[PDB]
Structure formats: structure tokens, C-alpha cells
Amino acid sequence: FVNQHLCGSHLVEALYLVCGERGFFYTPKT
Amino acid sequence: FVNQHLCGSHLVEALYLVCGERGFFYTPKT
Amino acid sequence: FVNQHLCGSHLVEALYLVCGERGFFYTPKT
Amino acid sequence: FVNQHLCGSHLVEALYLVCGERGFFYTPKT
Amino acid sequence: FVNQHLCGSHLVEALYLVCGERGFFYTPKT
Amino acid sequence: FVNQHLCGSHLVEALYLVCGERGFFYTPKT
Amino acid sequence: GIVEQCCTSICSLYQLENYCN
Amino acid sequence: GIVEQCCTSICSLYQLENYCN
Amino acid sequence: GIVEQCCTSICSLYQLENYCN
Amino acid sequence: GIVEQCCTSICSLYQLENYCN
Amino acid sequence: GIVEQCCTSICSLYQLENYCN
Amino acid sequence: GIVEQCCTSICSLYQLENYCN
Ligand SMILES: [Cl-]
Ligand SMILES: [Cl-]
Ligand SMILES: [Zn+2]
Ligand SMILES: [Zn+2]
């Protein structure tokens, strides 16, 4: 896997892909 | 606003949209 | 709901989510 | 180019792609 | 069709739309 | 990481994610 | 409408242009 | 869970806010 | 307009709602 | 092909790497 | 190449078509 | 955090994995 440059919803997409049925939490600063 | 089927990555995109900076959890197993 | 920073296709995604079966028009400047 | 099923947010993404600056309407009720 | 300004995954989306079942290759520099 | 159904544009998004700078091919006819 | 043309059936990128402004 | 509420059934953008932090 | 405002600044879902049909 | 491996069946992110260049 | 051109400048669907298999 | 790091810098899938439940 390659390093990722991921902003906004692209991060959430990536988390979704990576985590699958485990799901994930999205916790941005502030 | 409306109600629709939001699944998979679409679900998480909508979460991101609605929650944004608050953050969210996506926990499909419950 | 939180404020949104939405460019390009991300806006169209957001409009799609917000409007549902009502649909929407996308009318950028120029 | 090809022909494919474009539904929901995918449909609007393709509209955005094809129409861009012209803008478009997404009117599922017709 | 209008000209496109497409970065990151947006390019891959556009290629997917344009190419359909033909598929495509994505070959960024470096 | 997990295993999930990745179809259509979602498949190519995941390819983009996993392959990035390497690039990839999306060849649905095989 | 577009949904029938493009989702239920299939449509080309040229047909999608039918819905541009 | 969210999947049953929003994917299997349908849910509003307000219901989606149930899953914000 | 809404397209430029959402991108160069922010916009709310409630402002986006105005663009529904 | 990828569609059978990843869409019709399921595949891991490691299997997806099979289609990188 | 096409990836850099579409991002740093613009590109047309017709140029993208060149990248289909 | 991960959100800011992935955007302002890069991040790996392995770092993203930490955020799975
Ligand atoms: Cl972007
Ligand atoms: Cl889908
Ligand atoms: Zn984007
Ligand atoms: Zn989809």
C-alpha cells in the first residue's frame, strides 16, 4: 500500500474501505 | 430534506456531511 | 447540521443527499 | 464512450462530469 | 462535454465513467 | 483490513486508494 | 426521466448531456 | 444500527445526526 | 452563487436545500 | 477478473493490489 | 501525463478516452 | 490527529486502520 493524501470526504472513504464491517470513528480536530 | 437508502460508502459520506467537525462513528455491527 | 465546505463534485453529492427524490439543479457561475 | 447504469449519487456525479459549468438538473420525478 | 479539472480520485471516477466496461489504466507520473 | 464487495466506481476508488502512484488497471472484461 | 433512461435502463454520456442546462 | 436504519430502511439527515459525536 | 459560496467559503445544508426542486 | 474477485465475490485490499501497476 | 494535466490544468473527456482499454 | 495529518501531510492505510472499531 502507498501513502495517502486524503482530505475531507476522501478520508472517510478511505476509512470505510480500510475498516469494512468493523466500521470506524471519524474524529477531526476541533 | 428527505429520507433515502444510504448504504456503504454512501452512508459514511452522508455521515461526514451531516456530522462534519463533530465527527461520527460508523458502527455497522451495532 | 454543520456548515459545509464543498467544491466540485462534492457539492453535487451534498445536493443529492439534501434533496433526495426532489432532485435539484446545479447552477454554477459562468 | 460507453453506456452503463448510473444511479443515485453516481448519476449526479456523471451529470456533473458531463455538464460541469453549464450546470444541470437532476429531476428524478420527471 | 465540458473540460474537466480533476484531481486524485476524481480522475479515476471520470475515467471509470468515460471508459465503462472497456476499463482503463491509471498511470500517474512517478 | 477486511474483505467486502467493491463494485463499479467503488472498485476503482479502492484501486486508486491501494495503488495510488503505482497506478493500476481496471479491466472488467479480463 | 433521467432515472429511467440512465439508471433503470442505460444511457450514454451524450444522453446525460440531455440534462445539462 | 445505522445500517438497518439508513440502508436497509430509510432515514432522514436528522436521523443520521444520531451517529455524530 | 451557491456553487461558488460552498467552495470559496462555507455553506449550510439549509442553504443547499434552496436548490432542490 | 477483478470484477469477479472483488465485486461478485469479495476481496481484500491486499488482493486489490494485484491490479496495481 | 493525463493524471497531472487533469489536475494542474484541465482535460477533456476525449483526452480521458485515450486511457480506456 | 489522523484527519488533519492525512490532509496536510500523508498517511498510510496502516495508520487509518487504528481508527477502525
Ligand atoms: Cl477534492
Ligand atoms: Cl451502489
Ligand atoms: Zn474530492
Ligand atoms: Zn455507489
Image: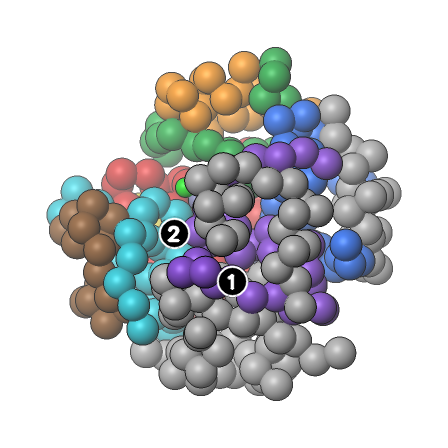
Chain colours: A red, B cyan, D purple, E blue, F green, H brown, J orange, L yellow
The quadrant of the picture occupied by the C terminus of chain H is bottom left
Q: Does the image show residue H8?
A: yes
Q: Position of residue F6 (x, y in %)?
A: 43, 32
Query: What's the residue type where badge 2 is placed?
Result: His
Residue at x 29%, y 52% (from the top left corner): B5
Query: What's the residue type where badge 1 is placed?
Result: Tyr
Mark 2 vs mark 1, foreground winner is 1
Q: Is mark 2 within 8 Å of ligand 4?
A: yes
**Foreground: F9 or H19?**
F9
Q: Which residue is mark 2?
A: B10
Quadrant containing ligand 2 reads top left
Q: Is H3 on the left-hand or right-hand side of J10? A: left
Residue at x 55%, y 25% (from the top left corner): J17
Residue F27 sits above or below residue B9 on the image = above
Q: Position of residue D12 (x, y in %)?
A: 53, 56
Residue at x 77%, y 54% (from the top left corner): E1
User: Mark 2–mark 1 contact, CB under 8 Å?
Assistant: no
Q: Is L12 on the left-hand or right-hand side of J11? A: right
Query: Is the same chain shared between marks 2 and 1?
Result: no
Q: Position of residue A16 (x, y in %)?
A: 38, 46
Residue A19 sits above or below residue B23 on the image = above
Q: Position of residue A19 (x, y in %)?
A: 34, 41
SS class of the residue under badge 1?
strand
Q: Does the image show residue F24?
A: no
Q: Is mark 1 within 8 Å of ligand 4?
A: no
Tag on residue D26?
Answer: 1
SS class of the residue under badge 2?
helix
**Foreground: A13 or L10?**
A13
Within 10 angstroms of label 1, few (less than 14), some, or many (20 or more) residues?
many
